[PDB]
Image (tube, rainbow over all chains, first blue to last red; front, side, top):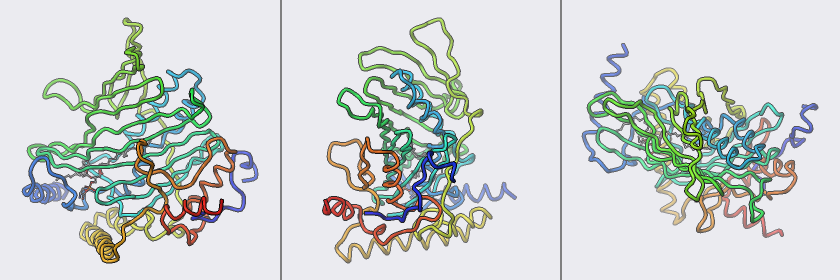
Length: 19
Length: 400
């Protein structure tokens, strides 16, 4: 069960160059 | 000016003290708003998490004794992040919650989730994790207020459990540290001037080492305020280091195997750069989310308007008393949204409700954390946020 909606991409250090 | 405000505050507090006796609690007594800082206790806990680098150093340290020292450094460093005058956090309402995150220099994030789980007696629970460094922290704060005469105290009965999820012990379980909290005193209320002190014992325990750190009070003539003293030991009677110094100045560590060596600098709290938490915009926060709930009170505090702060605070706490009345009428009791009651015999009263497998991909762990509550800008509450944790774990295994 989720109490929150997710960001479109789950942030990690492996996609911080995008962000 | 301020000397007149100080005299009237002094009298207001004497008028409260007049109706008490040493040993009784302050749960029934309303303290004035001019001793409040502008944050809830749920947010105040994150002050103690503002030095994640020491925890990262601990996680990458191979030697168990050195790793313990870095854990001690991480935990001791947070205490000096505290208000400057005699102030205390706002007492959270039942079910109040606070979420925050950190952007760490290594491009990872740390996540924090907390909720006030009980009002009588007060208790909040918190969860903190850095999934990409395999660091998880769970804890509870259980403050038991006491008037003691010339002093009063928050007797701090909570504790914290730290795990390095990818450092396995002999049972193949994560290496686990349990950390207790010293008591928080205000002294000088009867025949002096009020000052906040930490006191009594802080215990840190790992599978192979332990430290009992005494937070001392000043003597009449000897000693200093804010002094600490303790020994790092194994469980076989061997003493390795002595910690000394002041928890809001410089702390020192002496190697006990070399009797000639002098205590070396362990923590210089005035040369540390804390990393403050980030929080979602107020426009995205919930009605009983700490900063949003208390916004009108803290706005009045910031402009020193204490009549308004007192009235706004009364309306919040009066509403909570009415909600508690309604629960009695309905024949129900409060159950937290985000934390499940722990099984008997465990270190903590409450644990975050979401199952987060210890060894699963950290991207999956991050995704599961973000499903619990809104933490990052743009996340939205769902309907399910507001149902009890015990109903969310029933469904967490009912579909399985």
